[PDB]
Amino acid sequence: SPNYDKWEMERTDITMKHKLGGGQYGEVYEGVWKKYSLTVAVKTLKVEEFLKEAAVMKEIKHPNLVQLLGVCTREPPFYIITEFMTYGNLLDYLRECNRQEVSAVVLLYMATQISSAMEYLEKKNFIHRDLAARNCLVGENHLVKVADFGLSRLMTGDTYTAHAGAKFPIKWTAPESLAYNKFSIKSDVWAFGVLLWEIATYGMSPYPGIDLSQVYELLEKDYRMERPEGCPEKVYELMRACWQWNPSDRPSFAEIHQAFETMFQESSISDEVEKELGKRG
Ligand SMILES: Cc1ccc2[nH]ncc2c1/C=C/n1cnc2c(Nc3ccc(P(C)(C)=O)cc3)ncnc21
């Protein structure tokens, strides 16, 4: 039919149950797709930034990107409707987890899943622009997905320049981005370095006790966050690669993913055996 749009759903298909989290996600609701009795998440507005996130999510698809199910953007109130991620945002997940469940191998699994998604965006020539643990979502069996695509975009040049007044979450933001509003897949890699550090610390805040106003100056003097207690030497080396001052010196997400894939696989082996010991009590 002439007005068919594969993504546009009817608002009345969705029951809005309650606002998720603690207003901490803004206007994101747990809903039900009543036809199917499926729990969904729904972000609502009542614009350009909203519609831009809606547009971007139609273009990207991956096992580790939160899955768009549909939108209601023909008339207000606008909706973006996605799968429901059962455990919420990764930062709080890490802060409250049982570390016998969320063990060294699961920390590697998490980094493998996120870098898998970013390797995909990387070859799609997208940038994400807001990589952080608070912006990843967790499902069953430590399934992790990247979310929050409001600043994501398909790249036309090597660099995107955010508008003059823009402000950024300073502790995740690469030097060139802080100083010159320049973004690229490489400033995503820098933010991924910080995300790695959030994972390794089970969700500590970065640069603890360092004033936001001091951060760029410290970076320019080559200060970088210390290796967290318990963090594998190789993981920390990858963090430091992600935090190379010059963007072209940072690894690709292709390289990053491959390295974490390998480390994950090795760690799984010992984990699986340790599980089977212990079941033989
Ligand atoms: C609807 C929507 C539209 C565009 C988007 N871009 N990025 C995320 C989204 C979302 C939201 C995704 N999403 C899916 N499940 C979510 C969730 N789930 C959640 C599950 C459990 C809890 P608790 C531990 C308090 O019971 C809290 C939140 N919290 C926030 N966003 C979620």
Image (cartoon, rainbow, N blue to C red):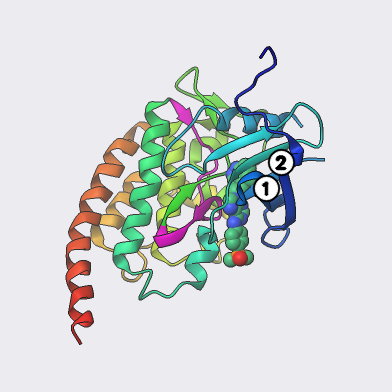
Residue at 41%, 39% in the rendered image: 118
Q: Amino acid at mark 2?
A: Asp
Q: Nearer the viewer, residue 100 or 180?
A: 100
CA separation in Å, label 2 and label 1: 6 Å
162 above or below 146? above
Residue, disc 1: 34
Q: What percent of the width, then of the height, locates residue 123? A: 37, 27
Quarter where residue 255 is shown: top left
Left or right of residue 90: residue 246: left
Can residue 27 be seen? Answer: no
Left or right of residue 30: residue 244: left
Looking at the image, is mark 2 or mark 1 earlier in the sequence? 2
* Quadrant, the N terminus: top right
Q: What percent of the width, then of the height, locates residue 84? A: 57, 52
Residue, disc 2: 13
Q: Amino acid at mark 1?
A: Lys
Is residue 138 within the magenta segment?
yes
Q: What percent of the width, then of the height, locates residue 35? A: 65, 44
Q: Secondary structure at mark 1?
A: helix
52 above or below 92? above
Labels 2 & 1 near each other (Cβ < 8 A)? yes
Q: Secondary structure at mark 2?
A: helix
169 above or below 280? above
Q: Nearer the viewer, residue 98 or 129?
A: 98
Left or right of residue 268: residue 196: right
Q: What percent of the width, then of the height, locates residue 36? A: 60, 46
Is residue 235 within the magenta segment?
no
246 above or below 123? below
Q: What residue span does the magenta drawing correspond to?
A: 125-142
* Label 2 lies in ligand 1 vicinity (Cβ under 8 Å): no
* Quadrant, the C terminus: bottom left
Can residue 237 be seen? Answer: yes
